[PDB]
Image 1 (cartoon, protein in one colour):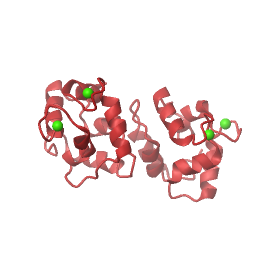
Image 2: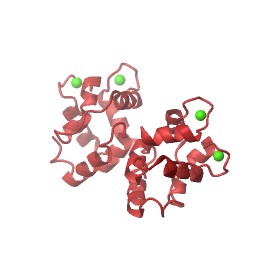
Image 3: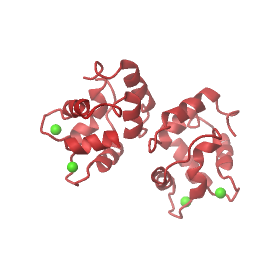
Amino acid sequence: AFAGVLNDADIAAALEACKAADSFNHKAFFAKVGLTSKSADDVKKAFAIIDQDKSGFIEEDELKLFLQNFKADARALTDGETKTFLKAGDSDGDGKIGVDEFTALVKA
Amino acid sequence: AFAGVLNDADIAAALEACKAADSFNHKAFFAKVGLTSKSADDVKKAFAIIDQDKSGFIEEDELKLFLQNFKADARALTDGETKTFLKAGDSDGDGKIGVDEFTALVKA
Ligand SMILES: [Ca+2]
Ligand SMILES: [Ca+2]
Ligand SMILES: [Ca+2]
Ligand SMILES: [Ca+2]
């Protein structure tokens, strides 16, 4: 769903880097795919894509499918990767990621 | 110190992938640099290189310098990366990584 608002080469490269089980690193991914330099406006747009049910949060089920937003046939994250990613972003410990928590994950 | 027993391109590619602060993932690295398919004999050789003082263990100070074994001017791992890496490998919880713990980190 971004393929068009991040460049295709960056996406490709970001996915190939984490093809192996447990090789995902969200900072590595965000840097390679090019989100880290994006405006807060574009980051909010990205958030909304990942929030598949538009609940206002990325719940754990959605985070597991994180890569599939970028390329539909991408692998699911392992449970291990998902928890690590949730724990880095979930600042208030409610077990989900809201928009400002996502912006911080991307940016800092 | 491997530049010669892993190929230069793989090393280069592995380092570029984790140039950003906190972007290191040891499974991603090991896969890209090509150690994961290596024999137990070559893995032991790699271990010995990383064990800079030849104590028989990679202590935390040595793990922080992990990348510098591959390319001398590579960055140090952050404290965050170092702890994560130590905690994935330190199976017996003595705070250092021995040869069989290293072989498991690489292989499985
Ligand atoms: Ca949601
Ligand atoms: Ca939260
Ligand atoms: Ca040592
Ligand atoms: Ca140990």
